[PDB]
Length: 29
Image: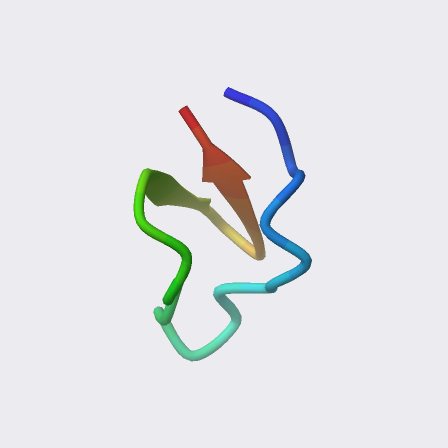
């Protein structure tokens, strides 16, 4: 639920395990 991945999923990518794409930002849970 938290954007603590340090990743944006603009292209639909989130590498950090637990990160979901809450476009355009990755949220870990």
